[PDB]
Image (spheres, coloured by chain):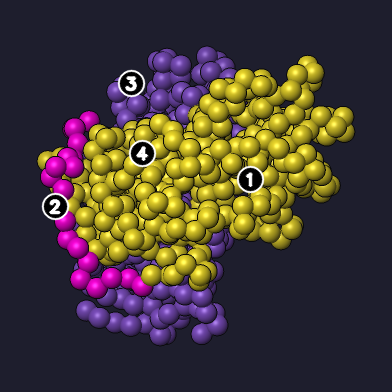
Chain colours: A purple, B yellow
Amino acid sequence: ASSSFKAADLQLEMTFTDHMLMVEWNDKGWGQPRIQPFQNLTLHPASSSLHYSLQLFEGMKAFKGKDQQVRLFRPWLNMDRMLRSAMRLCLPSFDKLELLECIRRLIEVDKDWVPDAAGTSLYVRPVLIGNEPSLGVSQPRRALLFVILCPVGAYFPGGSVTPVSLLADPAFIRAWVGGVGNYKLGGNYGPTVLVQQEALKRGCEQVLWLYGPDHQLTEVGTMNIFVYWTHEDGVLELVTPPLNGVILPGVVRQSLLDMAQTWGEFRVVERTITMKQLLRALEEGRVREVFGSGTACQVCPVHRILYKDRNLHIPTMENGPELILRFQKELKEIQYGIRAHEWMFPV
Amino acid sequence: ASSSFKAADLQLEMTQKPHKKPGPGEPLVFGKTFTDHMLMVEWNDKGWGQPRIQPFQNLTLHPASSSLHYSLQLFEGMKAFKGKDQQVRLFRPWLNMDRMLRSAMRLCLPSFDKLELLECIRRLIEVDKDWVPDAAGTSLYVRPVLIGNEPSLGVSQPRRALLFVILCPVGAYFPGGSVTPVSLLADPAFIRAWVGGVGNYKLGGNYGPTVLVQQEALKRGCEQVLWLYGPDHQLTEVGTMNIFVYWTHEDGVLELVTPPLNGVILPGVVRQSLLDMAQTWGEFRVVERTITMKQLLRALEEGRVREVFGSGTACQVCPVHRILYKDRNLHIPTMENGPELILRFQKELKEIQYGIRAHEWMFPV
Ligand SMILES: *Cc1c(COP(=O)(O)O)cnc(C)c1O
Ligand SMILES: *Cc1c(COP(=O)(O)O)cnc(C)c1O
């Protein structure tokens, strides 16, 4: 009472998994967390979740190693992000480690659902919605937190790393400074459906999100973007856009920056990336690799960019892709328990 | 893009046990009290289903519903008014219907026939007619919603959707017919929408992020938010209302100005009505042009501002008396100037809406 829900108070009642977590918030505080069979949600028609998008989510993977032990990849970063998203849309705060322990217990009940094939895992989807039975745009004192799980079977059609189809049109904007693009809110995704369809009929599989008067490369679909090149100063570097408001702080993004910094072989920085710099670098043969990063596709190569209906080839595949494969191998090693690391949380 | 549901295919299920009526003398909070019935229509792979109109009940949604994860949701807001002869009427519902599937087209929900939904809503209000209040400035708020209902976690076009309409009786925004002003926080750090964005559609996603800014307006002691856009600080919206400025322009001409529909402005029904009304009078210049803080600041020190107001069916016309910008107070002359134009707009809209003056803008139920 008077604070957050506790995993020690959990209520147990024994393509998605068999069970789900559910926690309710109402004025005075949180109710106890419930692990119950997968079932439909019953919401009032005036629920603020459906009218004013008082909704946020998270996305992380649970990996089954060779020793058959299930582990979550840096879940503390997902919990940090979830709480920041909650504060912004201006829902109840909760204790990050209590939600983690509740999710741990949920994955434990559905442990048989975690796949062990190469490139497979269990997708954990936590959600927090406003559940106020009112049409007023306000702080929603009733709320609902739920977690659902689902097995995912390899991103790539086989085991071969395949490059993806980008469209770069300045008329479409995902996020803005002073906006809400740095939080995983449902509201940022709905508007992308029409843009993705526009990309598909223009011969592209995904969208390269441009921002500002100087056409800054921000995100690749629902992934962060990275460019491995020799910059205009002659130094070999790995660059990704900074957290200035328009970028979603990805867990894989942070991990790639952390790993590359530890190696100390090349410069690793956060510095926006304009189409002017990319066009110049391509023409000068300074670009090595360009990729997207995210939970779905850990490291995802890009081979051409349709900018103002262009056919700009990105030489990612003819440069190995050396860094992508190194990142993929080291991540697989950490995630599937082949090497012990502080980044993994055992379930 | 697969036609529509028909009003002729609408069945009916009356309530077994009705909700409690508030009563003409007890406090009505906006959007917390609901009527006995609701409209609901489902869409899937075969197309649209039949409506029917059922008792007020909770929605049953799959946990992976795209409405809850990726905000595939939109809404409308219009009012039904009851005159002192018991006749119920809707204010320009065709425009709300026009604002509907444009919103659905955007994120990327099924199309429907505007007149078929209008007939279904008309019938729903007729069923719950006893819920429409009588008192001075009271009304029934009508809330149509269309959501994506896909049972998967992919960010894609839903193969399943749900359209529903709920009703709620609301009190007068201004008691006694006497308009009162609001103060606004103008902080450029928070942006509601951007060009190439989705602020020109009534989608749920544009509202959630405004809750924190509204709370920051409250803490800084200011009656609602003034939404600034760009490095030039363009005045765009007043909370969930369109903005209008009545002043003598820099060129020396008396005018009524409101921002143009360039992508950051929601095309309000009241906004369009005020423009239509002002143009029909032909007493002053009516123009759609960007308004900046620099222009407002210059007009204020030169004494050229007469009235500044917000527009949009909860309030119709809402006066603004103060704007907190750059930690400094800007006293807006709205109130000392009558407020003449606001009172004229309010009287005209009140007379049209409650049927005291007949107009083609009103749709009978
Ligand atoms: C989820 C997401 C990412 C990547 O985040 P990860 O935590 O690394 O999965 C990047 N950009 C957007 C827009 C996202 O939604
Ligand atoms: C609803 C709304 C308006 C006003 O629209 P009306 O149709 O006149 O009710 C204006 N701005 C915003 C941001 C709105 O949501």
**Dot label at residue A202:** 3
Q: Is mark 4 within 8 Å of ligand 2?
A: no
Is B19 a magenta residue? yes
**Dot label at residue B11:** 2
Residue under disc 2 on the same chain as residue under disc 3? no
User: Is residue B38 depicted above or below B199 in this figure?
Assistant: below
Residue extent of the magenta highlight: B1-20
Q: Callout 2: helix, strand or loop? A: loop
Per the model, the C-alpha gap separating discs 2 and 1 is 41 Å
Per the model, the C-alpha gap separating discs 2 and 3 is 44 Å
Residue bearing the label numbered 4: B363
Question: Residue B91, position in %: x, y?
Answer: 43, 40
Indicate the amino acid at tag 4. Answer: Phe
Per the model, the C-alpha gap separating discs 1 and 3 is 46 Å
Question: Residue A178, position in %: x, y?
Answer: 62, 43
Identify the residue at image location x=45%, y=58%: B134
- Could you say which is closer to the camera, residue B3 or residue B333? B333
Question: Residue B101, position in %: x, y?
Answer: 33, 35
Q: Residues within 10 Å of mark 3 (few under 14, many from 20)?
A: some
Q: Callout 1: helix, strand or loop? A: strand
Indicate the amino acid at tag 1. Answer: Cys
Q: Are marks 4 and 3 in contact (CB under 8 Å)?
A: no
Q: Are marks 1 and 3 in contact (CB under 8 Å)?
A: no
Q: Residues within 10 Å of mark 2 (few under 14, many from 20)?
A: few
Per the model, the C-alpha gap separating discs 4 and 3 is 44 Å
Q: Are marks 4 and 2 in contact (CB under 8 Å)?
A: no
Q: Residues within 10 Å of mark 4 (few under 14, many from 20)?
A: some
- With B305 as the anchor, is A262 left or right in this view? left
User: Is residue A124 depicted above or below A224 in this figure?
Assistant: below
Task: Name the front one of labels 1 and 3.
Answer: 1
